[PDB]
Image: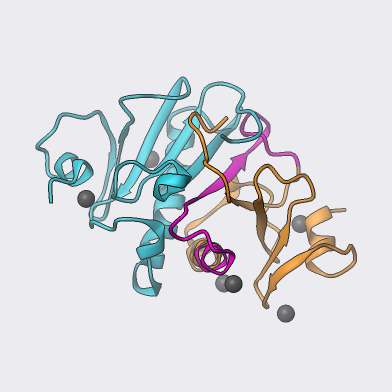
Chain colours: A cyan, B orange
Amino acid sequence: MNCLFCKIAQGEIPATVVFEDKNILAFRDIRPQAPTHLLIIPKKHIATINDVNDDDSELLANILIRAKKLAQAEGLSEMGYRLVFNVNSGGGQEVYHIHLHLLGGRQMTWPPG
Amino acid sequence: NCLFCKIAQGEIPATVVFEDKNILAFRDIRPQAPTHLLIIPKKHIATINDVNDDDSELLANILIRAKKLAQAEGLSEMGYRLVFNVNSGGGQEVYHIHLHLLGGRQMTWPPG
Ligand SMILES: [Cl-]
Ligand SMILES: [Cl-]
Ligand SMILES: [Cl-]
Ligand SMILES: [Cl-]
Ligand SMILES: [Zn+2]
Ligand SMILES: [Zn+2]
């Protein structure tokens, strides 16, 4: 209830949508941590990676595949980019709807937080 | 000439934590967190930029295996972070795809 990303996926909160298909939505993170910072989400509400079982694992892989296609469309792939899933508070997750971060447009450094 | 192919096939030793016909997971020798695992396909794919839709089964296997390794390591609730570096600007140095699993401390923002 009151999931921010479900609200975005339902058109109830403004966002810059860069990709949509029947299952997946991608949009800009409002607090970008790199010159381009995108989020790729399932439209289905799944709280954390720990809640992805075998029946949602193809969807999760397809989020990753869409992120790599989107990185090309957005001009990030030639220089390079980083993909991040955060899981729970110790992993940095704040919104409890799974999201893949796509960060690029500068050199990404090590460690990754 | 691929370091991770050699590890996958047993030609170079590693601290292996999981192996099946498709995947190998091992401890990073320069760990950036108390838990720092690398999960690789045995199949050689050079970079995430080369992924195709026929990789969905293997990529799902890698991601689910990461979830399961996080559980066995004690990180499911404490929290953890999964990272792919893609090409030089993403921090990739070895051109065989590898998923980083990091946890056992607070992971911070930005993620590098
Ligand atoms: Cl796209
Ligand atoms: Cl085996
Ligand atoms: Cl597989
Ligand atoms: Cl395991
Ligand atoms: Zn949601
Ligand atoms: Zn290889």
Instruction: Determine the quadrant in which ligand 3 lies.
Output: bottom right
* Residue depicted at 57% across the width and 21% down the height: A106
Choose between B47 and B80: the one closer to the eye.
B80
A38 left or right of B47 in image: left
The image position of residue A59, as x and y in percent, is: 36, 61
Quarter of the figure that contains the C terminus of chain A: top right
Q: Quadrant of residue A40?
A: top left
Residue A63 placement (x, y as % from top left): 39, 52
Q: Is residue A79 left or right of residue A70?
A: right
Would residue A2 be found to the left or right of residue A72 on screen?
A: left
Image height check: is B96 above or below A72? below
* Residue B69 image-quadrant placement: bottom right
The region drawn magenta spans B67-93
Q: Residue at x 60, y 28 (%)?
A: A108
Q: Position of residue A53 (x, y in %)?
A: 38, 71
Q: Nearer the viewer, residue A73 or B24?
A: B24
Above or below residue B16? Residue A93 is above
Residue B89 covered by magenta stretch? yes
Seen as rendered, the residue at the extreme left is: A12
Q: Is residue A3 magenta?
A: no
Question: Does residue B63 lie above or below A74 as drawn?
Answer: below
* Residue pictured at 43% horizontal, 33% vertical: A73
